[PDB]
């Protein structure tokens, strides 16, 4: 499935204590911008009511039958487009979420997870943001790969 509308809302359910709130907000907002910059999708943050994409920070078992695993390993996960838990993006609180160095970069991970929230799978290109393995890349030069663009535009272009 894909989202069958182009105005998509998100809501931050709770904040990781790893980062200042402003920096969580900014990383998430910029991550959505990565995908709206190459599609007709528009994303809006809401602060009450039910959003399409709920952003959650949780550790271990957190009520969706896909428990996290402590620091390392699975860093986050997200559900594909749909009602309810569909679209929601969960970040493992046992990671150390960061803006610049150390830990696991929240912006880069959110770009990957929102990709899943929108319906993308994984890429075989190590340069793709949808590559299955996280690695820190220079955020100043960050750019979707041709494969990422092809994938998202096949769904929403
Ligand atoms: C800059 O380029 C980047 C490239 C990749 C990433 C990146 C990759 C992976 C995760 S999370 C993860 C880690 C290990 C196994 C499984 C998962 C879940 C699936 C979990 C499940 O299936 O239960 C998933 O792939 O979303 C987060 C971020 C980020 C940036
Ligand atoms: Ca983990
Ligand atoms: Ca949802
Ligand atoms: Ca943490
Ligand atoms: Zn979850
Ligand atoms: Zn993934």
Image (tube, helix red, strand yellow):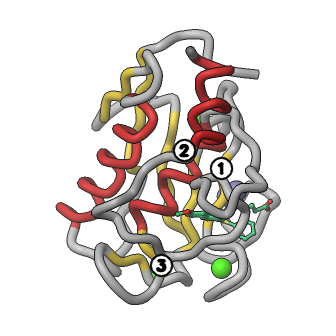
Could you tell whether 130 is left or right of 136 in the image? right
Q: Secondary structure at mark 3?
A: strand
Q: Residue furthest top?
A: 5
Q: Earlier in the sequence, mark 1 or mark 2?
A: 1
Q: Secondary structure at mark 1?
A: strand
For label 1, being within 8 Å of ligand 1 is answered yes
Instruction: Residue at 46% x, 62% y: name it.
Output: 108
Which residue corresponds to mark 3? 104
Can you give x and y, in whole percent of width and height, for residue 74 in the image?
70, 73
For label 2, being within 8 Å of ligand 1 is answered no
Q: Earlier in the sequence, mark 3 or mark 1?
A: 1
- Is 107 above or below relative to 100? above
Could you tell whether 11 is left or right of 73 in the image? left
For label 3, being within 8 Å of ligand 1 is answered yes
Q: Are marks 1 and 2 in contact (CB under 8 Å)?
A: yes
| Mark 3 surroundings within 10 Å by alpha-carbon count, few (fewer than 14), some (14 through 19), many (20 or more) | some
Instruction: Residue at 57% x, 55% y: name it.
Output: 129
Which numbered circle lies on residue 78? 1
Which numbered circle lies on residue 114? 2
Distance, label 3 to label 2, CA atoms, is: 16 Å
Q: Looking at the rendering, which quadrant does residue 24 occupy?
A: bottom left
Can you give x and y, in whole percent of width and height, for residue 63 in the image?
71, 59
Q: The N terminus lies in which quarter of the figure?
A: top right
Could you tell whether 37 is left or right of 89 in the image? left
């Amino acid at each position: 499935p894909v989202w069958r509308k182009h105005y998509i809302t998100y809501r931050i359910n709770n904040y990781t204590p790893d980062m200042n709130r402003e920096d969580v907000d900014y990383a998430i907002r910029k991550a959505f911008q990565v995908w709206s910059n190459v599609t007709p999708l528009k994303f809006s943050k809401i602060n009450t009511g039910m959003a399409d994409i709920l952003v959650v920070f949780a550790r271990g078992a957190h009520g969706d039958d896909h428990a996290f695993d402590g620091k390392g390993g699975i860093l986050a996960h997200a559900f594909g487009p749909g009602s309810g838990i569909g679209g929601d993006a969960h970040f493992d609180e046992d990671e150390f979420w960061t803006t610049h160095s150390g830990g696991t970069n929240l912006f880069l991970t959110a770009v990957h997870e929102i990709g899943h929230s929108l319906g993308l799978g994984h890429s075989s290109d190590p340069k793709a943001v949808m590559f299955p393995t996280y690695a820190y890349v220079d955020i100043n030069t960050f750019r979707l790969s041709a494969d990422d663009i092809r994938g998202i535009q096949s769904l929403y272009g």
